[PDB]
Each structure stands twice: as C-alpha cells, then as structure tokens.
Length: 26
Length: 67
Length: 181
Image (cartoon, rainbow over all chains, first blue to last red; front, side, top):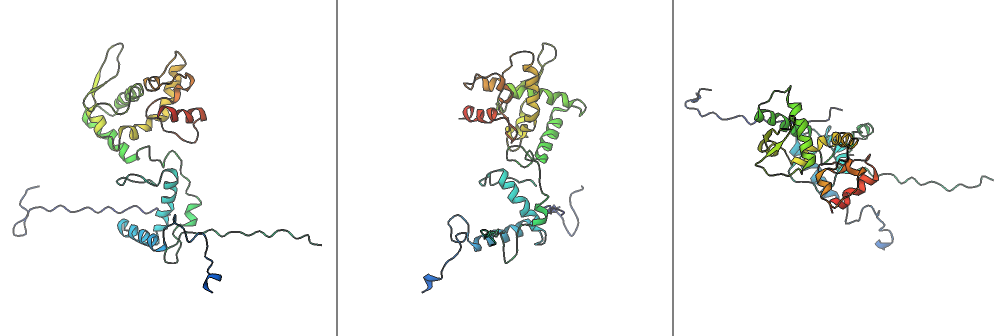
C-alpha cells in the first residue's frame, strides 16, 4: 500500500574533461 | 464431431476485447517502461482503471494520469 | 413438500489476468475511493498548477504575501472574457476607478496544458463570486451573454472555464450542451 512512484533517473551531466580532469571551473 | 462440443464462452470470442497475447504484451511492456516490481504493479493498474472510468479512453498521447 | 426454489446461478466475475495471475489488487481497490474532483482530464495536476503559480510570481516579481490580490483579479478578469486571449496583451484590474495592467505573456505561456485546463481550479470559487454579485444587481458573464443565452438565474454556471461534476443541477448540466454546440 505504498502506491509505487515511477523512479526518477537523473542523467548525470558530462563535464568536458582532459586527462581525467574537469576543464570548466564550476 | 468437434462442432458438437466446441462451445466457448461469449466473453472470449469477441471483436471488442483484445486477445490474451495482445493484453499480455501491453501489461508486460508497461512494466518495463515504468520499471516497477511485479509485486507492486497491481497497485498501479488498480488506479489505471479508476482513472479511465472518470475520463475517456482516447486521451492525449503525451500527458499524465493521476492516482 | 419443500416447494422448490429456483436455483441462483452466480456468474463468476472475470478478473483480468496475465500469465495466470490477477492484475488488479482486490484489497487496495476496496478502499481506493478518491474524490471525483481530483481524477479528471479537465483540471490540471497539482504539479502543473504549482509550476504556473510559482513561475508567474517570478515573472511579475511580487511578494507571496501580495500575490493573492493579483490572482484575486485574474479570476474575475477571465470570467468576463474567454480563456484563450491574445498571447501578447494585458489584463486590467482596478484601484478605485482607475486601471492597472499586467502583461499577459507569462500567464498564458506557463499554463500547461492550456489556460482553460489549469484555471479550472478557480471554477468552483467562481460560482460563489457570481452568486454574490447577482445578489445586488443583474449580473451576467459576457461569455454566456453573447452565446444566444438569456436565462438569468443560470448565470452562476455561464463562464468559459466551468468544470462539470456530479453535483451540478440538471438545468446547469443541460445548459452547456447548447452553448458549446
């Protein structure tokens, strides 16, 4: 009796990266 | 011979109701899209009938239904 | 001497079933009884109405303590006109025999799915306002006014965004057949 709620899938954003390091300074 | 015992229910051979295969595909495909466990889906379809009584059966393709 | 009674044949109901398993949950169904007002295709969902009400607040830049005033005139304005106006334009309110205007672009653009289907939240209250006005003068909304209609008492049910439920009088319920013909 918890009336299932459709799970929300948050598509993780893809920071540009070089040599395993983010380029933009958030 | 076979005709004398071939007596199916009227409920079964109709042009209104969908075949058991087509209903099975719809019920399974909805489960994959919503991603809900089979033990909890009875709840979801429990509100689907109630929602479709209060409205039509040809709504907008894009939209939501409320429980 | 038992006077045979015609036997009763109970036609067993046919639960929908997939892979030999009932789909409906009979337990939950016996207490799942929501209001008719809630599950409708006319009224917008509480989330969509929340987005519209919040987004309008950001666009107009008015404090939440004063916005009730602004929406207080929005319903009255939409009774006197339709619910599908020009995207670019204004709606008028009133401060003591003077006009103040507000842009109509934010109101009619953040109204999903349509302004009628989201402003129908106000349709219940609008009956109280119209009845109050009609108690001091002959009041008729301009929509039903110019819809070939002539009845006076019915005017409580003669605006564009009226939603119909099981408690509307038959005279009201049969009316919308002719106006929306």
